[PDB]
Image (spheres, coloured by chain):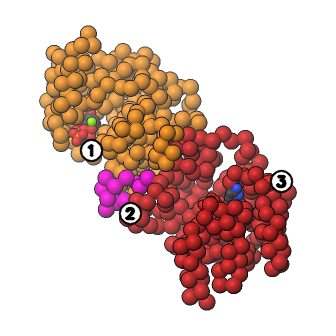
Chain colours: A orange, B red
Amino acid sequence: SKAVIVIPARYGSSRLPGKPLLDIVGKPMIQHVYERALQVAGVAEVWVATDDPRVEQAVQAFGGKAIMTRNDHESGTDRLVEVMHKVEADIYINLQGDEPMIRPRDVETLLQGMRDDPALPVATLCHAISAAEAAEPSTVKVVVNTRQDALYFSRSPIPYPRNAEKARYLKHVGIYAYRRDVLQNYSQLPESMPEQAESLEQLRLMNAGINIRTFEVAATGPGVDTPACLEKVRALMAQEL
Amino acid sequence: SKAVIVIPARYGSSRLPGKPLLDIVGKPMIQHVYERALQVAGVAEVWVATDDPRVEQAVQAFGGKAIMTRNDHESGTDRLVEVMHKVEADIYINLQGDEPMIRPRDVETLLQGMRDDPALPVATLCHAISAAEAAEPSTVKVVVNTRQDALYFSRSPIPYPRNAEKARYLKHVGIYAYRRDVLQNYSQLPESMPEQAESLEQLRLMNAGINIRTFEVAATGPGVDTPACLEKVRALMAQEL
Ligand SMILES: Nc1ccn([C@@H]2O[C@H](COP(=O)(O)OP(=O)(O)OP(=O)(O)O)[C@@H](O)[C@H]2O)c(=O)n1
Ligand SMILES: Nc1ccn([C@@H]2O[C@H](COP(=O)(O)OP(=O)(O)OP(=O)(O)O)[C@@H](O)[C@H]2O)c(=O)n1
Ligand SMILES: [Mg+2]
Ligand SMILES: [Mg+2]
C-alpha cells in the first residue's frame, strides 16, 4: 500500500495572487507545506502540482518535487487526477498549498484511517467549532454518523439549532485521502445540483454514493487567504519556533 | 412480499384534543385517511394504531380495523414497532393520522420503491418547494443523491445558496416504508445528536447507516395540526367534492 502526498500550487489566485511564493518567515509558503509534508510518516513521495513556472522554479529551488500540470483545471481535485496518472500510488493525499500550519500528525491520522479500512474510498478531517463559528458561510460544516461517515457538507449551520443546547458543530478541514481507483473514475463524475449551489466540490462524490469518512482533530490554526490572518500565520509561524 | 399500512392515531393533541375524531365534510379525520389507505393497491391490511377506546370505537363504527396500543407511546414510530410485533408483514407503511388529503398513488409509488429494491431499508417521499418556502424551520428539507438516497434532513435551507440560481429544494413529505427487520432493531437504536438538535426522529436511522430512499411527488395537501389548518383542509376537501 504505497501512499503519496500531492500539493496543488497554482500561481493564479483570485484573492491573493502568487499566494504560494509568499514569504512566511524566510520561506515561501509552499515550502513550509512541503517540509511539513516530508515529516509525515508512511509517505513514499511528496509532490507539488504546479501550473506556473514561477512556482516550479521556486519549488525546485528548495529541491522540491516539481511536476508541471495543465493551467486550465477548474479545481484542485482535478489537478490531482492529472498527477494520479503519472505518479503511481494506492493512496493519494491532497494537501492544500495555502495552509502552512498543517499538523503532520493530523495527516498521519488521515492516512491511518485509509489503512485501517481498505474499503474506504475517501478520508477527510474535521474539528469542533462553536455555533458562532458555524454561522459564517466561509466556514464549512459537516455532520457524521456513529461510524464517522459524512452525512452532508454545507455552508448553512447544520444541524439546525432547534433545541440549540443539544447542537454541536464541526468545521471541515479541507484535506483528503483518495483511493487511486476513486480518482480514476472521477472525471466521469457529473457535477451535482447541491455541488453547484453550495459551491462545494466534495459533494460531487456524495452525489455518487462514494463514502467519505471524517476524522476529528484539535482546533487547527488559520489557513492563508485573508492577508489579515496572514499576519497571525507569520506571528504563529515565527512564534512556533 | 406482504405489506401492511399502519395509521397511528393517539387521542391526545396540544391544540386539537380528540383530533383523530375531528369532523371533515361529514366523517372523522381518521376515516378519511383509512378509506384512502384502503384504495392503495398491493396492501394486504390497513390498521389504525390507537391509544384511546373512543378512538378505537369510531373506527370500528365505520367498518375499519383497529388495534389498541400502549398509551405511553412517545412517538408514532415507537407505536408502529408495537404493531410490528402483533401484525406480521415484510413491509410496513406508516401513514400519519392527521393527513386526510393523502394521495393513494403517492403511497403506491412509495410501496413500489421498496418492492423494486429488496435491499432497501426505508423509503420516504418529498416534493419540490421554492427557496422562499425552504426558509421556514417548520418545513423539513431533504437533499439527495443520483439514486435518490437521502444525504441529510434539516430545517436549515439546504442546499445553501452560494450560487442561488443552482439551488433547488425539496420539502420532506413525512410518510415512511419500513422493512420489517428495520423495525425489529429499532428500539435498540440510541438517539443521535443531530436528531436532538434538529428534533427529527428519522435522523436516528441515518446515524445508524440505515439508508432511506426518497421518492418525488407533486406538492401535497396540508395536514391537521392547528384549528386554522383544520378549517384549511375542511375547505379544500369540500371543494374537491
Ligand atoms: N485549478 C486549481 C484550483 C486550486 N488549486 C489549489 O488549491 C488550493 C486552495 O484553493 P483555493 O482556496 O480555491 O485558492 P484559489 O484557487 O487560488 O482561489 P481563491 O484565492 O479565491 O481561494 C491552493 O493550493 C491552490 O493553488 C490548484 O492548484 N488548481
Ligand atoms: N405518542 C404518539 C405520538 C404521535 N402519534 C401519531 O403520529 C402522527 C403524527 O404525529 P405528530 O407529527 O407529532 O403530530 P402531533 O404529535 O399530534 O402534534 P401535536 O402534539 O401539536 O398535536 C399522528 O397520527 C399521531 O396520532 C401517536 O399515535 N402516538
Ligand atoms: Mg484556500
Ligand atoms: Mg401533527
Magenta region, residue range? B156-167
Residue B45 image label? none
The amino acid marked with disc number 3 is: His
Q: Which residue is mark 3?
A: B85
x and y percent of residue A90 in the render? 47, 30
Image quadrant in which the C terminus of chain A is located: top left
- Looking at the rendering, the quadrant in which ligand 1 lies is top left
Q: Residue at x 38, y 26 (%)?
A: A219
In the depicted view, which residue is nearer to us: B237 or A148?
B237
Q: Which residue is mark 2?
A: B131
The answer to whether marks 2 and 1 sit on the same chain is no
Q: Is residue A114 above or below residue B154?
A: above
x and y percent of residue A23 in the render? 15, 22
The amino acid marked with disc number 2 is: Ala
Tell which subunit mark 3 falls on. Answer: B
Given this view, does label 2 or label 1 mark the residue nearer the observer? 2
The answer to whether marks 3 and 1 sit on the same chain is no
Considering the whole magenta stretch, tell me its main secondary structure. loop
x and y percent of residue B3 in the render? 77, 64
- Cα separation between marks 3 and 1: 57 Å
Q: Residue at x 42, y 49 (%)?
A: A204
